[PDB]
Image 1 (cartoon, rainbow over the protein chains, first blue to last red):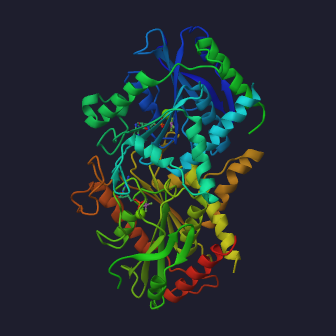
Image 2: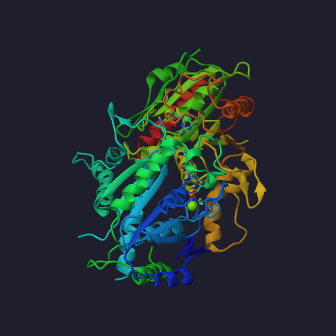
Image 3: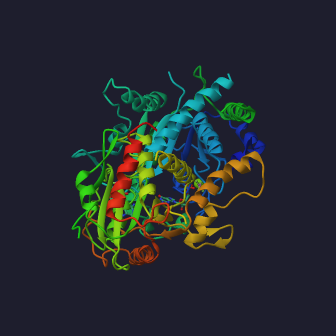
Length: 290
Length: 288
Ligand SMILES: Nc1nc2c(ncn2[C@@H]2O[C@H](COP(=O)(O)O)[C@@H](O)[C@H]2O)c(=O)[nH]1
Ligand SMILES: Nc1nc2c(ncn2[C@@H]2O[C@H](COP(=O)(O)O)[C@@H](O)[C@H]2O)c(=O)[nH]1
Ligand code: ALF
Ligand code: ALF
Ligand SMILES: [Mg+2]
Ligand SMILES: [Mg+2]
């Protein structure tokens, strides 16, 4: 049916535009949708992980260069491998912090759309969880509220942090951590009444409230090789064997746990209803708030 | 001289303070100084690369876990390996973006001090040059002017060190040296629209602020899944290319990094560095 990805939201010269051809395809799919979007800094292996969710070696194209490759937001609608009669919709995004673009405002919009359109939202980083990403997640979360206002049980997405090229010991304060406990460690509140105790707390309170469920997975370097240039065409046997497992566990969690996308009121989102969200939210951005 | 590093600027509960023991060591050193500082996100291999400048296996301690390890600003004064009668002062810094700390303002001060105190400033990142790193570098150079106001260029030279570098050095069909990658990342936009001007203004300020720039790439130090034992490994246990890239970095620092200088052209020795540390730490500890 849908034989490869297609640009859903174009990103050309500062302007975010819905692709009519993608909208057409969406308007033909009447099945309910599980929507999994991924965002993170550019050149962090996002497109590759998304191809795993499709069960394919190739799909969203990777790019082997210091330049950004994924632009705007791409979609790939494929049969949901565990829930009969559902469609799994994969949303692959333009990486954050491209120095060729140099446009933060534009980053925020893409980030925001990804959150607004998803039922599972995947934030992808290398090595560590880091405050600057947590600051940005919080900002975009709040912006998401302003966009919903401009038009106008929970229908906010569940949350996954994917840690790439993970090489450090999962320990803190003498104590081992699971990946999940590392995430909740990172969102832990300062006990104090004190003032700054409150500045520190407040973003964390907001992220914890916005995303109802949370999950964290670590991934080894895919390959031992010093270069990733040939990745698209290496079979599992040529990859690091614990990377392969880690990817399986991740996919299997997404397949088992990611909920059907839902409108406020509880109505389930299918093609025509996603098409109508895309336009609503792109129009709301094309206007003028920040 | 110094058998190991020590804390120069402590960082406790939002307070940055000079270590009197460190100042006392500074005040005894009459020789002119080359000062190399390193900044970047936390857990990014900063302390390891600094130890290679000191030609020791162990030194600034690394730490194995997800938690930050280097706190505040540490110093290591060793004889300059290429300039007789000079001292090489290495400043290793608390990494940025620590989720345990969750204090951007503290990050800034540490970032500003490193810039203010150095004669070569090394900014260290994984994989790419990110715009978020550029944005903060701009922010901090401006802050720097503010701090200097509370009380022939003497601004440091600049080096971007790219870690775990795995991507093809190539942009728009054309192959890049690391240096051409840095200058590509600071390229200005043709036109003169509002948003051309916004894009340009950070890039103009960085390029003006740092007289010389330079860029190195480093492979992953090891192939092993985990970094844990990395204090202990010899050069033949490491990635061969990483060893050569480090040799090349070090030999660039040794050859090219200038003596630290005050405005008016006076060369900074221990007592003059001491007085800079106090001056800048007090200005931060006062009220903006
Ligand atoms: N460092 C790293 N790069 C990866 C990984 N997976 C794929 N890549 C590379 O990341 C690039 C795509 O990243 P994206 O811009 O989609 O975030 C491609 O070069 C792809 O080969 C990974 O696990 N770690
Ligand atoms: N990913 C990565 N980590 C490294 C590298 N060199 C050393 N490390 C690790 O980086 C951590 C220290 O980083 P720092 O907090 O000083 O920036 C230690 O765990 C050290 O073993 C490197 O080249 N790449
Ligand atoms: F750099 Al990309 F998707 F190619 F973030
Ligand atoms: F996490 Al560090 F120096 F130990 F930035
Ligand atoms: Mg991509
Ligand atoms: Mg360190």
